[PDB]
Each structure stands twice: as structure tokens, then as C-alpha cells.
Amino acid sequence: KYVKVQDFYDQLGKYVLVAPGKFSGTVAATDLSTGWTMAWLAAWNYGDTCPIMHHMAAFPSPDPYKEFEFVVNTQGGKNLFIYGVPVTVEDPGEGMKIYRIKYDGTRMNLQRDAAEVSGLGLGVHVTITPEADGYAVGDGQKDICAEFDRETDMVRYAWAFDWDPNVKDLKRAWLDGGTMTIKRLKPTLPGGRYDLQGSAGNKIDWELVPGGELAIEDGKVSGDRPLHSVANDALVFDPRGKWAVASMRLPGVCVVFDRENQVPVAVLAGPKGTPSQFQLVKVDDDTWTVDIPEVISAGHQAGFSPDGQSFLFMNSLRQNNIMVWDSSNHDDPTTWEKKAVVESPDWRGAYPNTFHMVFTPDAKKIYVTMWWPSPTPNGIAVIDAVNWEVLKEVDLGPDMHTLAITYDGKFVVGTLSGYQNTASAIVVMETETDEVLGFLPSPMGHHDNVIVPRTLEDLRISRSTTT
Amino acid sequence: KYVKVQDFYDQLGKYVLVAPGKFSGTVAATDLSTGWTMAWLAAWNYGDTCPIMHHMAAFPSPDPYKEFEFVVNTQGGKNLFIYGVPVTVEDPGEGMKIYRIKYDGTRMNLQRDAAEVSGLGLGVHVTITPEADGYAVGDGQKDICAEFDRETDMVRYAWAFDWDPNVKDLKRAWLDGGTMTIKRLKPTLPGGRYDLQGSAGNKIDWELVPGGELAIEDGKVSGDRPLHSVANDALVFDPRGKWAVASMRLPGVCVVFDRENQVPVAVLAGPKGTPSQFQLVKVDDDTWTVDIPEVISAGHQAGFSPDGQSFLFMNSLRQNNIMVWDSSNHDDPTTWEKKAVVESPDWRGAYPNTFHMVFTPDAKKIYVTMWWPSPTPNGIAVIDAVNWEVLKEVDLGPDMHTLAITYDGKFVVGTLSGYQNTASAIVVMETETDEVLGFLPSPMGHHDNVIVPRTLEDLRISRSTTT
Ligand SMILES: [Cu+2]
Ligand SMILES: [Cu+2]
Ligand SMILES: [Cu+2]
Ligand SMILES: [Cu+2]
């Protein structure tokens, strides 16, 4: 007679979608086998006065439906003013919170704020270590990343990054190059803690938007110290262990760190045209530098294929493509060498902007975001990861964000977020012939989403090895 | 191969569902033809410091996808402490806002706070007048209801209700009878404004929950004036025009009001066992009284069938049934006689509590809510409104709130809201053989929802004639 939406959910199976909602100030888990939201959480109700719920990542649980834990961070300050919502809050809080929350089989519970426990507030990407024993956050306003311990929320190590332009004027500070310093950040407060919550640390007073390097160069982004900015975005993890990679938007490079010995060991150069790497120079036991002749393009998204064998960093802005290194040699990242660039005619200038990606478990395909400012249709591009070529692009709607995949490989689940004021949805695509099955309602401006992994192997294609 | 969710939405058609989300702080509209959320608004963004978004109702729009306008009010104070979210807020806002919001075919726009325009702040049911030229709001803490003009947001008339118990002890205050006063409530501030925003007016410090009539009796509800409460809930409208009916929870009556002459004309007695009406006595030009020998039962849900020929009030609490009156004589409500009572073996003392309803366009059936405290399954009873009998009950999940219906009469659309901390959903049932088609995600604690009407006729089965 009639069609039952339960038939759609029957095919997706018992996966748990989690996603935060940015200006909605909520986070929510959804049952993809029934269409229910399992639980949601409103941070205002906990006294947060700028609850911009931003990025997030879930630890694996053997049964997400009885329990799971996740990490979700917030942004604050003038970040509240930069989207199209005519916000009337005067003096909002400062965000940079890192909330630990546990779903217990009925409700979500706010465990604590890790930014308080560690001393270190960081407001961009959140990922889980491949061993599920901790997590990392990055922040492009203060240019710090750190890997924290799951059980205590204390920082295992934290790196601060600094730019020293060869030309001291914002228009040229990146294009004509400079030296980046890589600096061990050491705790300064009792108990092993930092003094870097909320805005403490900030160089620029809000996070650079997609294309937002142009803005910083044109002197349109305020802050104390924009000339020193690199805009770190993320620390993503090699699935094989040992190394974590920090992405720096403005200087177009990624830094490979030794997690156990807490040194950086290599710098990979993003733009097509430049070598595989630049030279890392140790200055002292806590200080390294790297010189860059010119920044030919800012980069964004960074991540490893599930087997560890390829590493990717996206050029965005002046170039627009995916640079791929061969990371085959687990024993020494200073050998990792460029082996492929994914290019496509429509990939010119800042838009479409490729800010997020997910591999299929066997690693032969990639789903990658194509973002544009309103009104141009946003979408997904499907990449052949064996030959490194675009297979197809699907237009979907406004403001495309992240992409997650069911662990059996079969369905891609993505979020579009209305720029915080217009249409928002969850999108489902099947990966056998890459077609959209449609949209589920989602009143939230998500800039992240995940499916709760069950095993350490599922994390290799979740929020761990890519953003 | 795969089922597309678009197939389920193709059978629903271009209807727009709207609902607010109570603790979530937000409000959202969904395109039931594509699964997208069309847009959503987070009240914290406009500086509201207790954005419990409560009840709402939408003006008809000839094309809602192009634009439509709605009203959504808030609660604050200690309402924020009444649910199991371990809220930690120091100085919560007082709530009782009445927002005017307009969707402009891209975004939601906050137009203003009707409670600041009028001075009169009310936080329970919001309904639209059948001519779509104004709206009404009730409040069970202050015991006031009013009709507001749509263009100016100024009060057309408002009424204040007061209880004068025969026994001055909260335990007997309603059981052993009393007198209720109906007072015309007049502006005290310049320009025809009230001085009654926020907590001003409050007799008890929070709204009574389902079954909370026993809490007030037991001295569990603090406030300044509990012995005087009646807990007004709503002012629903005869779809034929002329009359509005205010429901009074604690004394178990409804008062019929003549909208244009600004006087009450009749009082309907809810519990089975009592006559059709108690006698309204005029005291002076602004004051009427009505005596009740004893209150056998509190009531709650109240509303008209779409042709106006039947009027319903739900006994909850000490009886649990639907009382029905013959309202076919539109010239004189003092002739409305009880004509039936719907009863069911399971409907004994408070739970399930039947607090929400919607009619089919032809008025031949009613979908009514059945609410229990966690953990018993809440759901929907289907009522034969030709013979006044229950047809079936369907169990759904936690915390069942309101129901709407598509104006072609084909699909019933309801909200479950997880007691603000667990599972939430929208549910879809087809009215042809009353089977549930399944659930769409909705991370929101809705106590309201509407499908946006397109004509005046549509309002006869929207938030106008029933809550
Ligand atoms: Cu990023
Ligand atoms: Cu973001
Ligand atoms: Cu009610
Ligand atoms: Cu309510």
C-alpha cells in the first residue's frame, strides 16, 4: 500500500550517527536502524554562554547502544559574529572548551571539561588516537596542537607553531615565504597544567573560514599577531601507530611528529611544484625551524588512507588539488615522497574547497567534500584512490561539511549545514554505484559527524586518520 | 538494490512541519517532501538566557516554501529545574516570551517579542484565531489568557482567573469545591500595555506537569498563591467564529467567551457525573463568578471538531476520559449539552494522560496522545468520533507530546521528546488503516508541532481548534 520509512533504515543497519550543531548549541546521536534520535544535549543548560559546539570524535565501544564516550569542543569570542545570523549577544564567553560526554544507553551525560582539567583550550579539529587511548585537538587561532590521555584528560605533549614572514606586510607574509618555528609547549601551572583556556594564546580573533587566507592577507581578520599566524587545523594519526601529523593552513605544510619520543621528524610540502619535503632544522631540545622559499598555496584537509600506505594533503586557495605521498615506509617519514596529485578542471581557486574526506575500508575510493559560499550547490566528489582521479561529482545542496562511512563500507553519511541559517540535512549515498539515497532532517549546523566505531580497525576510517 | 528515502517522502507531499524543542533552545521547519530541514533558529543567539521554547502555532500561508509566519513562546524560572537534566544555571531568565518569527523562504527571522510589545507575558498554549488575524496565549502559573492582534501584537482582551477554595488547605482545595472568579484584566501601563512580563503575575513557580495536580495538593509546588490557582492552559477557538474557550485544569471546567463583546457566556463542567454547565453569575461589568460544589477531576485537553458541532474536554487525574458536548447551536453556548463520554478499560487515574489531539478533515476520527512517565511506552489512541469509542492504541516510545495532520487527512505527524534527556523522534502514521510508517530524527524536546496551513479551512485541524 504505502511505503514505510523503516524500510530505508533496515538497509543501513545498527549504526549510531553522532554530530554537533555549531550555532544550534546542541549535540545529538541518531539511530540509523530506526530513525530515532537516541539522545541530544544542550550545552546552554550547563551554563555555557557561547555554546558553539564544533568538532568531535567518538571512541570505539563494543556496543554503542548500551554506552559510548565522545569528545566535542567549542568556539567562542568573535567566532559568534562571523556567520549570517544577526546575533545580539554582547560579551559572549570565549569557548575553546573540550567537553567529554558519555551516552549511557538512555541519556548523554556531561562528564567534565578537558580544557579545564588540562589547562589547554583548543577549538578546531578533534581526533582519536588509533589505540583509542586518547585524542588530539588542534586550534588555528592560537596555533597549538596536543595529544591528551583518555583517562586523565592530561596533555601527553603539545606543540606551538609560529610564523616569521620574509616580507613583513600581510599581503606578502605567506606568498614570499618565511621560517616556521616548531616549539615544545611546557605546562606552567601546578599539576602539569597550562594557562591557555578560552582566548589565552589567540593570535587572530576568529578561525579562518574556507578561503579565509585571502581575508587575513587583506588585513580583514583582527588579532594581536596575524603576521605570526600559521592556522594549524588538525593533528591526524597514522593508523599503524607511531606518528601524528599536524596540518598548517597558511604555510601549506604538514609536520610529522614522533608521538612516543615527542619530536617532529619531517615537514611535508603541500603545493604541486614544490619538493616532497622541506628541511627540518633542530635549534635546541625544544625548538625546531623550517624554512619555506614561497608559500605557493595554503593547504587544508590532511589524512592517511586506512592501511597507512598513502598520505594526503589538499591544496585550497591558489591551488586546488589533492597531493598524495607514499607513506609506505612506516619506519622513517623522512622518506615519504610525492607519488600522485589528484586534479580536475573545476578545481581552480578557493572553490570548490575540498575540506573533508573519508576512505572506503579497502582504501580504493575516497569521498571528498566540495564546499562553496551561498548560492552555488555544494556536493561530494568520488575519487578513484587506485589511479588518483575524480570519478564523479554529485550536487547536493548548501554548505557541505563532513563525511563518515558505515564500517561495512556500504553507505556514506554526510552533513550539510545551511551556513547556520538555511537548509540543513543528513545525506546518505550508497557506495556500490555511488548514488544518493536521500536526506534525513537535522536542525543543526554540524561541522563534524561520526559513526560510533565498534573496533580499533573501524577507527581507521573515522575521526582518527582524517578530518 | 537499495531503497531511497525520497520514496517515503514522495508519498507525503509538500507539507512543512514546524516544531520547537523545549530544552534544546531551538525551533525548526522540515520539508516533508524531501527530508531537509528548511531552517532553524537557536534563541541563545539573540541573548535569551533561558530559551525554553515551548508552544507555537503557524499563520496559513498560500505558499509556506516561499514564506510563513509563526508565534513561539518560552518558559523560564524554575521550569528549567523540573525535568531530569542536571541543569546548572545561576540566574536563569524568567521566560514567558512570545516570539514572532518569519521564514522568508531561506531563513528564519526573529521579528520581535510580542510580550515586550504588549507587556503581557504568557508561557503555555499558543493558538491562531480562525480568521488568521490574531493569536491567543494562556498561562497556568499566572492564570491569564488573552487574544492578541496579529498586525500590532497588542492585546484585544485578556482574562484572569482566581480560585476561592471552600476548604483553605491545599489537599482539599479543589476536591471540596470553591468559587472561580473571571476578571477582565486591564492594561495598567501607558499606551494600553500590561505590566506582566516574565515572572510578574506568577502564583506558582513552575507549570504543573501531567499529574502535577497532586503535587500542588501535596504542597510540593511553591509559589506565592497556590490556594488560588486554577492553572489555565489554553484558549481554543470555535472554527465557526464568535467564541473562544479557556480551559481550567485544576477546577475541571472550560469557560466560553464571546470574542467581540468581551464577556464570558458559559461554563462547561468537565467530569462525568456532573451537569453540562455550572451557572455563571455576573458580579459587575468586569467580574463574573461560578461555583463548583466539588471538583471530581482536573481536566486538560480541550477543543472543537472542525465543523464546530462537537466540543471536547479531557478529564485527567481522578477520572480519565473524553467528555463531549453538542456545540451544534452556534448562536448560544448556554445550550451546549453533554452528549457523550469516551472511556477505556486502561484509562484509570492520571496515566495514560490524554493531553493532545487532532481530528481528520471529515471529523470522523480523532488521534489522541497517551502520555506516561518513564519507562512505560507512550503512544497514540485512535478514536471513532461517530460513535465515541476507542478504535485502537499504538505504542511508540518515550514522552509523547502533540499530533498534527496533513491537510489532505492522509498522514498523522507526531513528536516524542524523551523527557528532554532520552530518545526523541517525529512519527508518521497513515490514517487509512492507522499503521505507523516509522520515525524521522528530531534532536529536540518538542511540546508542540504544526503543519503550516495553507488556507483558513486548514486551521480547523491545526493549532486553532485544539491543542
Ligand atoms: Cu579543517
Ligand atoms: Cu567549523
Ligand atoms: Cu495543555
Ligand atoms: Cu510543555
Image: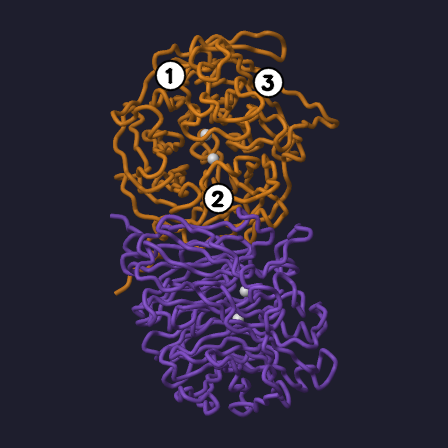
Chain colours: A purple, B orange
**Residue situated in front as seen by the camera: A359 or B36:** A359
What kind of residue is marked 2?
A: Pro
Amino acid on which disc 1 is placed:
Pro
From where the camera sits, is residue A225 visible? yes
Question: In the picture, which quadrant includes the C terminus of chain B?
Answer: top left
Residue B86 badge: 2
Tell which subunit mark 1 falls on. Answer: B
Label 1 SS: loop
Please indicate whether residue A163 sits to the left or right of residue A405 in the image. right
In this figure, which residue is indicated by the disc labeled 3?
B262
Q: Which residue is drawn at 27% across and 42% down?
A: B435
Residue under disc 3 on the same chain as residue under disc 1? yes
- Residue B211, image x, y percentages: 40, 27
Does dot 3 land on a helix, a strand or a loop? loop
Q: In this view, does B296 lie to the left or right of A261?
A: left
Pointer 1 local density, CA inside 10 Å: few below 14, some 14–19, many at least 20: many
Q: Which mark is residue A13?
A: none
Judging depth in this view, the residue of A462 and B325 nearest the camera is: A462
In the image, residue B134 above or below residue A9: above
Q: Which residue is pictured at 39% across the width and 53% down the height? A: A103
Q: Which one is in front in this view, the residue at disc 3 or the one at disc 2? A: 2
Earlier-in-chain disc, 2 versus 1: 2
Q: What whole-number distance in Å separates the C-alpha atoms at marks 2 and 1?
A: 37 Å
Q: From mark 3 to mark 1, how far is it between C-alphas?
A: 27 Å
N-terminal of the two: label 3 or label 2? 2
Callout 2: chain: B
Q: In which quarter of the image is ligand 2?
A: bottom right
Q: Distance between the residues labelled 3 and 2?
A: 44 Å
Instruction: Identify the disc placed on residue B271.
Output: 1
Image height check: is A347 above or below B140? below
Does residue A307 appear to the left or right of B1 in the view shown? right
